[PDB]
Length: 171
Ligand SMILES: Cc1ccc(CNC(=O)C2CCC2)cn1
Image (tube, rainbow, N blue to C red):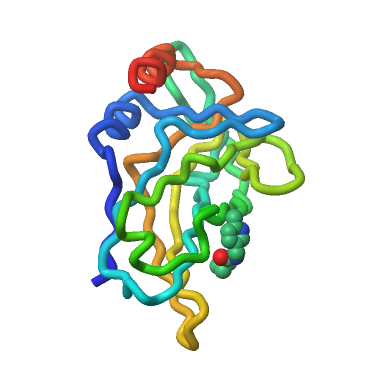
């Protein structure tokens, strides 16, 4: 069976217990922590492209009110995010399974922009998601996996200083 697991879940859970925040910039900001995924059960000889996207976890705008994150009252539908293709794609199963697949080069922005960077809505909550796409073969297949542990709110600057501190302590 194709098995997908989160590397360094320990550390993600520290961020999650405080409510994680990720900075977004007009040019794009790399994520910390970085999403690293353990994959087994691929055909070492089959070809796969790894895709990363961000699901809007709810339909609300969030605000840091008196030291606490709280959702707005006025939900709007959230158009799905664009997909980031791992730069190592497309590649053999063996390649993907020899070390954690690390999305270190994805950049999160708040502005519609040339290419690469993924645009998110500031003050929305996001759940990272990957797609493993079997390519080249006749039988195209997709396996998707969500990472609740890696939920965050997109912010233009950190609101919770406990997050600012953890981000520096562990980088
Ligand atoms: C950074 C980068 C790497 C590879 C590619 C090639 N396209 C794919 O792999 C498609 C996604 C499913 C097939 C484009 N961009």
